């Protein structure tokens, strides 16, 4: 029904690519992309539970949290050392979840020509598997 | 040593004014000011504990969290429906705490001429008392 | 709605004086008074929660708990190293609570002539309290 | 030590149980040892405290174990609002002692068919049986 | 039901205690009822499960209560890796029954001085004494 | 480092097949196999944590737990309605774990001729598993 507290690798179902903080960069504005599996810290996301049912995601060691500065269609998911966006992670199929912020679903954008693309908010076309680290 | 989980009114020691979400406005960018005591929801802050020792503050009913878009000297504390800034709430004297974001201490700005002023980050001149609601 | 577990300074709203174990004396029969703010151990009260909603208060380091040997109108609140009274801490206004024992509300008595006076129980809410996290 | 829970508390030396005399909820009611009944006045809720101490309260009656005068010879009673912080220390596997203010509880068997209140000594072990 | 904790488990009808025969940690070791010792092979850790069931494990020996064949007459044993999910239901205040697969545990008193393994019946109550 | 309490689909890395209670049969002696992903109840394993670090697995709704009647090399993993084996679930790589009973690692056996084969214990880590939250 819900994702329990723990640390996970987060794999997009449609592309088999993993949620990835670009270059493990801890600076604000660093895009959260989907990338080939590495299992490194910038692909390990700590899931923090909140009493209202929402979730927050933070990278191990880097300590940059999933953050969206402007919650509107097309807004980009980034990593931020101090700011975080409260997310709604809802089950769609057994073992497959959607992630949304402010009612807008996360859309996985596969890399193009070797350059990763930030996850964006759509106006569920992207599902995610939460694999325990 | 630390502020435990709970809902609090947060009174600035130096001015006896309370942390207040301006006009109870739930929109992003709404300033967090200090204001005369009302005890209404925009002055009731839920303190959420995190395993790393940080804290996050959310208004009751309004559900806007304490959020700082740019963590630099002079940056303003606002309320945001979906975003939140992880804070460090440290004891200074018995019953008196400092609040900081990204290592920068919160500075209480008393209202001027009837207009509230947003709490800002200084480069501890502002202490806070956490009163259980 | 309720006071969560923690350690608090407890200030009387009507007088801005703090719940205070007189002279920090750990002996039985030591009055719990209201006194000027100090922030010392005899003004730090550990709030212990009970499953029925009641609360118990104990001073930090001194380890003397709020205690009422005779729960009747006029009875005095003291500190006791081994005995304690289960209290009902009820919200009256946002951020302002009343304290009662056996259904009798705590009454704050301000000092007279530089001498503190014990909190007492009023007959069957003239005193309210602010719980300030230590 | 004894974990949080509700127990029947039987004295080892007598096989008699901690008993709030007559299920009387008023202050001053003696805490005695009595033949087993299993009723509410023999069901003691053990509450844990972070300093390691314990407090006991009867089920439904809501009278807690209380010692007004914590000196040798003082009597254990039940009180609807007041309670005494106790130390319940393991002596043998499955057998515990109870003390208030460093003074051990002493189980007093009935004299002439009438119950006698537990007293503090300046000798009595207890088995905590989960209700 | 029985809360989580470590207990000595005494059969009411015999006053004998649940006992891992000879403290033997190997599979197939009988779970018997035996005279009180208080040793590790009589200390049972009660683990709670969200469905209401319970599992028992001996302290230090780490052998859990296990029933290979859950049918009338099946024997209760200790096993280092396998365990049987049990239902421990209150019958009277302070007295519990134990069952596996809907079949009650039956305490078997020693025959000729030798312990007899607990068996499942198609009659035995237990007191959980906190260690 | 460890698998937290929850309900998981458990996929074998080397074959991308999922731990599967054959035919969802709740009877004792029913093999635990690896099978094509379905997401059904017989592929949903509740992970119960134990204070010593061990773990137990139980199918949702069917209520049959992972069980090894004979813990030896070659012994088969089954589902059992009332008996269960305490397991050691150890991290090998990030996101990839091994499962073992009595110190013997679980070995995934892929189906042959459209017939599933039971997970077995290898002699004293050829099989790894991904725990996917349901
Ligand atoms: C080790 C490390 O930081 N790896 C990252 C990788 O995970 C991905 O984010 C990539 C984007 O160009 O940048 C780096 O190579
Ligand atoms: C009830 C309500 O929203 N009150 C607020 C008050 O708390 C303060 O924020 C003020 C700033 O001008 O605006 C309103 O009056
Ligand atoms: C440090 C200390 O014990 N201070 C106390 C103070 O808190 C108050 O109780 C006063 C009453 O006359 O007695 C002392 O000075
Ligand atoms: C039911 C009930 O309160 N029974 C009590 C019993 O427990 C014991 O206290 C006895 C002392 O004379 O008085 C009554 O019989
Ligand atoms: C210490 C120890 O294991 N003692 C056991 C005892 O508990 C009981 O199992 C008996 C059966 O013959 O065998 C031994 O004496
Ligand atoms: C729904 C159901 O029980 N499905 C199972 C499937 O999961 C697998 O175990 C297969 C083995 O032949 O048998 C059945 O079809």
Image (spheres, coloured by chain):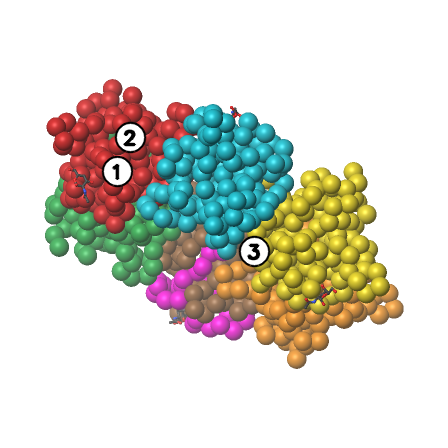
Chain colours: A orange, B brown, C green, D red, E cyan, F yellow
Residue at far bottom of view: A123
Q: Which residue is at the front of the view, C96 or E44?
A: E44
User: In the picture shown, does residue B85 fall above or below E103?
Assistant: below
Q: Residue under mark 3: which chain is it in?
A: B
> In the displayed structure, does residue A7 sit left or right of residue C90?
right
> Could you tell which of marks 1 and 2 lies nearer the N-terminus?
2
Q: Residue at x 70, y 50 (%)?
A: F77
What is the secondary structure assignment of the residue under circle 1?
loop
* Quarter of the displayed picture in which ligand 6 can be seen: bottom right
Q: Residue at x 64, y 72 (%)?
A: A92
Label 2 in the same subunit as label 3: no
Q: The magenta stretch spans which residues?
A: B23-48
Q: Is residue C66 visible?
A: no
Query: What residue did someone put label 1 on?
Result: D36
> Residue F24 location in percent, x, y?
66, 63
Q: Which residue is at the front of the view, F116 or A65?
A: F116
Measure how far apart labels 3 and 1 are at the Cα level. Answer: 57 Å
Q: Are the two marked residues, 1 and 2, in contact with CB atoms closer than 8 angstroms?
A: yes
| Callout 1 crowding tier (Cα within 10 Å): few <14, some 14–19, many ≥20 | some
Residue at far front of view: E112
Q: Residue at x 39, y 24 (%)?
A: D91
Q: Is residue D14 visible?
A: yes
Question: Which disc, if any, is residue B86?
Answer: 3
| Callout 3 crowding tier (Cα within 10 Å): few <14, some 14–19, many ≥20 | many
Indicate which label's residue lies in the foreground, 2 or 3.
2
Indicate which label's residue lies in the foreground, 3 or 1.
1
> In the displayed structure, does residue D83 sit left or right of residue E119?
left
């Amino acid at each position: 029904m819900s994702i329990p507290a723990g640390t996970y690798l987060i794999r997009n179902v449609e592309s088999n690519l993993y949620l990835d903080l670009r270059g493990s960069n801890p600076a604000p504005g660093t895009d959260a992309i989907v990338w080939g599996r590495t299992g490194n810290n910038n692909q390990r996301w700590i899931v923090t539970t909140h009493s209202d049912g929402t979730r927050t995601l933070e990278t191990v060691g880097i300590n940059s949290s999933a953050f969206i500065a402007t919650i509107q269609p097309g807004g980009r998911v980034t990593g931020h050392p101090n700011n975080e966006t409260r997310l709604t992670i809802t089950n769609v199929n057994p073992g497959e979840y959607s992630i949304s912020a402010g009612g807008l679903l996360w859309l996985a954008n596969t890399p193009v020509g070797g350059t990763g693309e930030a996850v964006t908010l759509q106006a569920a076309q992207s599902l995610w598997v939460f694999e325990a680290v």
